[PDB]
Image (spheres, grey):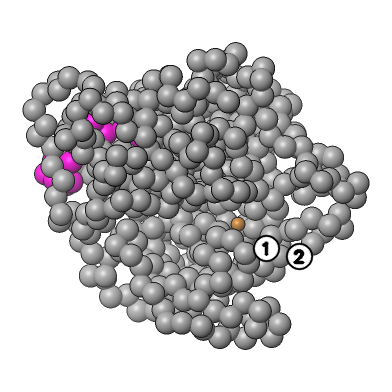
Amino acid sequence: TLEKFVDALPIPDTLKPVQQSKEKTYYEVTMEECTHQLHRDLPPTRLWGYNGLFPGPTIEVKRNENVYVKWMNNLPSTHFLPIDHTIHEPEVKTVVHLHGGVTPDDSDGYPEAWFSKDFEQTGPYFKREVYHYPNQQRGAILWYHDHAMALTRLNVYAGLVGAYIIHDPKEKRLKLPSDEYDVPLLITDRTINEDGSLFYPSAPENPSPSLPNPSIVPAFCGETILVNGKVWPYLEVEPRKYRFRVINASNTRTYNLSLDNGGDFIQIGSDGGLLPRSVKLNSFSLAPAERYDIIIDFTAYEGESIILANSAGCGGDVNPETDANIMQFRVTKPLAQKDESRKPKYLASYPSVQHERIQNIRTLKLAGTQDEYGRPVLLLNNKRWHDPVTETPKVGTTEIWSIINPTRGTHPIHLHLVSFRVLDRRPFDIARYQESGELSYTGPAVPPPPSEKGWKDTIQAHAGEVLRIAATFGPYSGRYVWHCHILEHEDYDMMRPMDITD
Ligand SMILES: [Cu+2]
């Protein structure tokens, strides 16, 4: 296996606007096939990258900054990963979703608003080439990635992911670590062939001859872990406080992170922004598309090498020599200045200060069926993506969504547009629910832990539990989506339209 910790962690450069004035900032980002070396001992890997970079450039904006991004497809007309034509026109379709963005619907990256190279062909919901992000929302770590219908798992795996940070100047007074000391960590698992090329399965193992070829698989677990486009990298840090924006940009894999010197993380933020109170943690779970905004204090660890370790399995127990490792910090960089940063306990208002009336309660089941080839098709409420819309909240109203998961694993559920509150999780009798549809609880409700007392947009719905969240659907109306963020599930067919009506 590749030798761990021999390449430095790349820090993606911050994108510079093509045009900028007090009234508007305009960016251009072009999707290109490109080659980059992913590890010291591999030949360069062919990838698809935003501005030909993997990951894409980090975009940084202010709260309320009037931003435009023209996302362009300059990719080849043929894909390089295995396309399964039986699950759903040009072969290569792309569209960019700013994950976490409070965004007008035609700029949200709807799966059917895709475009081919140079916008030659566009999907039925395409309206515009240049996307608009008003950023009228809390400071937070967002990220952007491909969202095209039936191809998201392939386009994202090819390398189409990047970070986007909204800075709210009202938070500057908190003195959180900043600038060179505020570093995004985009984690992506991959399997790489000897010749350096990416490997993505063209079918399940044990391929019944009843399967199409290629065939979609229900989950992808990569053999190697990359951070910011390098396999098991190291980062040299100064012995002081750093802020890390940790993003899970993997197709399926969930991580459970810790530090091998027993140090703590101080969580300061979740998907939707700063938590009301900082939270000291020895470990945390991070499923696909979730973000943790954390401080690590290396002050007392000068000279040490500390591994950011992983204990979550993917298709099996973790292997101590490979996927149990994410990256290595080396506390060997001399201090450039006094550490004037802080790790305050009091960070922001509690979401619970809000007292919205509950307009509606929706009950949603995570289910599925089996196709003519014997494969599982995962479905939200047993509806297909193409079935008539059923999730139709009224603009400005607040709803409780009750997500029932009778399946064997966790599904990370993402709602577009909004961030929401976690109310509680409660275990139920699976067999009974499956036989009769009756929901019978086997224990009391459990309120969220501190890490989930703030705002979330992608939320783990564990097996054998009902998860309740509360969301206010606004400020925009229109057609969005909600879906599982295991990409292999999303593309077949665990995604539904969401109409916020006026
Ligand atoms: Cu799922």
Question: Toward which corner of the image does residue 69 lie, by quadrant?
Answer: top left
Residue depicted at 71% across the width and 27% down the height: 80
- Crowding at dot 1, Cα within 10 Å, few <14 / some 14-19 / many 20+, comes out as many
Residue depicted at 33% across the width and 65% down the height: 449
Residue depicted at 87% across the width and 58% down the height: 372
Q: Look at the image and tell me whether residue 309 can be seen.
A: yes
For label 2, the residue is 369
Q: Is residue 497 above or below residue 424?
A: above
Residue 445, disc: none
Secondary structure found at label 1? strand
Label pair 2/1, CB-CB below 8 angstroms: yes
Quarter, ligand 1: bottom right
- Crowding at dot 2, Cα within 10 Å, few <14 / some 14-19 / many 20+, comes out as few
Q: Is mark 2 within 8 Å of ligand 1?
A: no
* Percent x, y of residue 78: 74, 26
* Percent x, y of residue 228: 44, 29
Label 2 to label 1, Cα distance in Å? 8 Å
Secondary structure found at label 2? strand
Q: Is residue 499 left or right of residue 59?
A: right
Q: In the rendered structure, which amino acid carries the disc numbered 1?
A: Leu
For label 1, the residue is 379
Q: Nearer the viewer, residue 196 or 181?
A: 196
Residues in magenta, as a range: 170-184
Q: Nearer the viewer, residue 369 or 273?
A: 369
Q: Is residue 92 left or right of residue 178?
A: right
Q: Look at the image and tell me whether residue 130 can be seen.
A: no
